[PDB]
Amino acid sequence: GSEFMAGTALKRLMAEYKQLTLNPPEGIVAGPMNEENFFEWEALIMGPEDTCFEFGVFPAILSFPLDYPLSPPKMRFTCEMFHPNIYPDGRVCISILHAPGDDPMGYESSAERWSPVQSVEKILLSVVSMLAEPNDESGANVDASKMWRDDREQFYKIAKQIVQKSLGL
């Protein structure tokens, strides 16, 4: 079949890489984890500056669909994390990573959802902001949601643990 959409996705991905290379954004680093496969990217998220996740170095994997940029990639942290918006297996669940009207009724579905005008940079950018600002309204991690809403002081405690664990301590 016309692996034309795949080829287009590839070129789109190369373009975004070129751009991240010549115009790197702060606290982010991402790129194919192997030249041979531009659909599997490795990334590093640095913990937001004055947040409970500061000084943390969180690696992640972005897997891009063959129809990119029509659909968003899947993003999964590779280290341990404790966030309301992150699943047990590392999967990141935020609006920009869901197809418009993907599912789960959304008003703001209209603007904060995936679209060809988005980019891995913007994705990574919002994930960073996700770290710096949680939203207990994401059953990704029930325990993290409950804790953040109820006992937040303990949340900050476990978060600092997450950072240390990422540092290899």
Image (cartoon, rainbow, N blue to C red):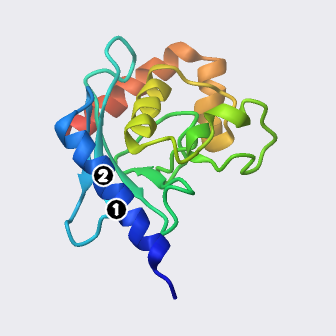
Whether residue 169 is visible here, answered yes or no, is: no
Whether residue 95 is visible here, answered yes or no, is: yes
Q: Residue at x 32, y 26 (%)?
A: 47
x, y percent for residue 65:
49, 65
Judged left or right of residue 46, residue 82 is right
Indicate the quadrant containing the C terminus: top left, top right, bottom left or bottom right: top left
- Is 94 situated above or below 55? below
Judged left or right of residue 40, residue 168 is left
What residue is pinned by disc 2?
15
x, y percent for residue 33:
23, 60
Q: Label 1 is placed on what type of residue?
A: Lys
Tell whether label 2 touches label 1 (CB within 8 Å).
Answer: yes
Quarter where residue 152 is shown: top right
- Is 114 situated above or below 47? below
Judged left or right of residue 145, residue 130 is left
Instruction: Name the secondary structure under disc 2.
Output: helix
Judged left or right of residue 50, residue 68 is right
Q: Residue at x 22, y 33 (%)?
A: 24
Quarter where residue 20 is shown: top left
Q: Label 2 is placed on what type of residue?
A: Ala
Q: Residue at x 19, y 42 (%)?
A: 21
x, y percent for residue 77:
40, 48
Q: Residue at x 35, y 11 (%)?
A: 50
For the residues marked 1 and 2, what is the alpha-carbon distance in whole angstroms?
A: 6 Å
Instruction: Give the class, few, some or many, for how many residues have Cα within 10 Å of label 2's Cα (few <14, many ≥20).
Output: few
Instruction: Name the secondary structure under disc 1.
Output: helix
Q: Nearer the viewer, residue 9 or 131?
A: 9
- Is 155 situated above or below 8? above
What residue is pinned by disc 1?
11
- Tell me the tag on residue 73: none
- Is 71 situated above or below 101? below
